[PDB]
Length: 287
Length: 287
Ligand SMILES: Nc1nc(=O)c2c([nH]1)NCC(CNc1ccc(C(=O)N[C@@H](CCC(=O)O)C(=O)O)cc1)=N2
Ligand SMILES: Nc1nc(=O)c2c([nH]1)NCC(CNc1ccc(C(=O)N[C@@H](CCC(=O)O)C(=O)O)cc1)=N2
Ligand SMILES: O=c1nc(NO)ccn1[C@H]1C[C@H](O)[C@@H](COP(=O)(O)O)O1
Ligand SMILES: O=c1nc(NO)ccn1[C@H]1C[C@H](O)[C@@H](COP(=O)(O)O)O1
Image (tube, rainbow over all chains, first blue to last red; front, side):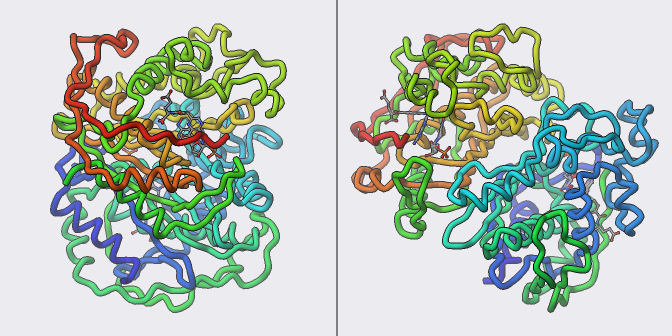
């Protein structure tokens, strides 16, 4: 009854019943449209164990989002290079963004979460007091009206899409409270099952822990919903290796001090305890 | 293996395992966060049979959305009164919209789908050439790049939310093509299982048929994803009546001529064939 079995079974389902589907990157995929999994957050943390997940990257990326950043260079210097390709000179130029500085991902998560509706200029522009701070609004609504069925943070901004180096794979998330517990559902339009998905699950589970902490709630469930759930054709053999491995108990996430605001979390405030994954499995990134 | 069994089983699941959850309307609910169902659209149409669904309302509402309307009065005169309460003088005044004309629902689906990002003024303002026509963009993308994993229409607009008489229950939808078939996934943040959900399923199935028709594709699946899936406490006895009834085969939807553009569909272009539902079950609307 290990929660990780849901992920492994989604992979198996795509390998057995998915359709071949060509893709933007020219790699090719096996694909299923519409999946859902539920990861309990109660006294455990869904950091996958059948391969080592890059937790440092997960944590630094989320802190960077919370700062409102859309500058990959700010994250890269942490040793977290996950957005570097998307902000590179040549990739940017390929999308027509030759005026843009390297690293400028466009009006993606950090900007939409903190400044939705503002006019994007450059990654380093001053957006203070502009647009909707959806992140803080979610927090405030959970505190004042936990029954609210409208507690959403939405990165999908049709007006801004043409400026984004990668339109968000994570279109929106919704929070929910019952019985003292905070849950989160992610709508992921496009899930690279081998590379992005394990990382993304940890990201939103971590966000839920952070928000529960500052709202005085306990973490409940993370519900992961997928649009195009796909396995790149060059991830088939790596995932078949992964599927042979037995899950180990999920770790725990500890928050090491009482933090009052989302902005105040720091890397050293977190400890993953009891994480004993199987070895890293290299999965190439389709660009 | 009837598709309707998924809906009936979601209702049963909420009745048995849902949590009590207070709500905005003061009615109270039994609630589950995170559900998903898949309704085939292949040679049948998921218009529920265990009660008669208001198909005329479904069809007229969708045509009204496609016209870009946010004026409930335009729909009401069709004998489709579903948005009238939300646009009524007293409801509007209760939300602080006393300057607003009756019927003005704010910048909801018709406006977001046709004019995302434009500045909302009144329901009757001229928005020609303003904002993003997401509906037409989806259509064009399906035709030119069916593999695209970004084919989204999003009604959730954080900037505009304060002006909406009801923030969209249908936050976004995504389209997907494989094997000549068009699928659609709805992210429904809040689902009134007794009243709205059966109606909403038919709406998005109908939208998928329309878009498949004009793009030369065959309908595939409608994937229905729910956030707060709930049964109002005063719908429990009506739904228990419904659950006793055997499903009948789903009907077929026929489109009676070749229509070239989404704007050109008319009520008389559609015929539901073979629909033999059990009788209407009155479910009161929580306001
Ligand atoms: N094709 C594709 N798939 C993605 O999942 C993806 C994408 N493109 N573009 C950007 C992006 C942003 N997120 C991420 C997340 C993790 C890695 C990644 O390379 N993680 C490796 C570890 C890297 C390291 O250890 O330094 C992994 O194996 O999870 C990259 C991008 N994700
Ligand atoms: N509480 C609540 N639930 C909803 O589902 C809902 C809401 N509020 N506010 C507005 C709204 C918009 N959609 C709809 C859809 C159908 C009906 C409705 O009354 N349908 C009846 C048939 C009405 C008739 O036959 O004229 C039904 O039983 O489905 C109302 C609102 N839906
Ligand atoms: O799985 C993903 N998660 C992300 N987290 O940031 C980024 C996107 N992705 C994956 C989904 C696709 O394989 C790819 C984006 O390509 P697109 O769906 O064609 O935009 O990256
Ligand atoms: O089920 C719904 N579908 C709609 N189609 O237009 C409209 C909203 N609803 C239901 C969900 C809730 O019961 C209610 C909206 O209340 P809220 O979730 O508190 O915003 O209406």
